[PDB]
């Protein structure tokens, strides 16, 4: 009963902020790496950011570095994506995903569970 439920997507102005949340359950959350991917219609899923089980090490797509912050809360079993400087290029459906390992990678097929997605639109 692995469940990953995203929320927080919506319309945001390029001079604003938006925080995505992913409520995880049905597995030992703090044993796995977690990530965010995004997808534009007709295109492949693009890696956005990921972090290891503990949150101590992170990785970001070069195009979002310095604008987004990934974090997790290992008591609440929640994964976050804080968009501090959103841009029009960020418009996409965002998915949270569980890595198959305690760490992470940039390959979508190495994440074994996926959420339902949340649309982000940057005007």
Image: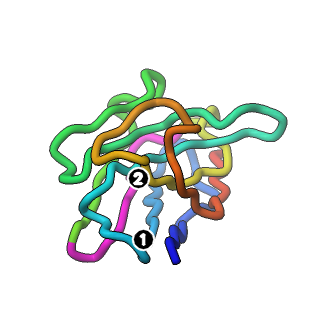
Is residue 83 in sight in this rendering?
A: no
Residue 93, x across and y down, in percent: 67, 50
Q: Residue furthest top?
A: 62
Specify the segment rendered in magenta: 75-86
Q: How is the image coloured?
A: rainbow
Q: Label 2 belongs to which residue?
A: 81
What residue is shown at x 38% (from left), y 51% (from top)? 34
Element assignment for label 2: strand
What residue is shown at x 50% (from left), y 45% (from top)? 111
* Number of the label disc, if any, that sits on residue 24: 1
Q: Reply yes or no: does residue 76 show up in magenta.
A: yes
What residue is shown at x 37% (from left), y 41% (from top)? 50
Residue 106, x across and y down, in percent: 46, 30
Quarter the C terminus occupies: top right
- Distance between the Cα atoms at labels 2 and 1? 14 Å
Q: Residue furthest right?
A: 42
Residue 101, x across and y down, in percent: 35, 45
What residue is shown at x 60% (from left), y 33% (from top)? 46
Q: Nearer the viewer, residue 25 or 48?
A: 25
- Report whether 96 appears left or right of 53: right
Q: Nearer the viewer, residue 34 or 65?
A: 34
Element assignment for label 1: strand
Q: Reply yes or no: does residue 4 show up in magenta.
A: no
Above or below residue 26? Residue 105 is above
């Amino acid at each position: 009963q692995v469940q990953l439920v995203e929320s927080g997507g919506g319309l945001v102005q390029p001079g604003g902020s938006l925080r995505l949340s992913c409520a995880a359950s049905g597995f030992t959350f703090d044993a796995y790496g977690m990530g965010w991917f995004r997808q534009d219609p007709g295109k492949e899923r693009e890696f956005v950011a990921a972090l290891i089980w503990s949150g101590s090490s992170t990785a970001y797509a070069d195009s979002v570095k310095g604008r987004f912050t990934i974090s997790r809360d290992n008591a609440k079993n929640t994964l976050y994506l804080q968009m501090n400087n959103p841009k029009p290029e960020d418009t996409a459906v965002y998915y949270c995903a569980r890595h198959r390992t305690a760490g992470f990678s940039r390959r979508d097929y190495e994440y074994d569970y996926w959420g339902q997605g949340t649309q982000v639109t940057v005007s």
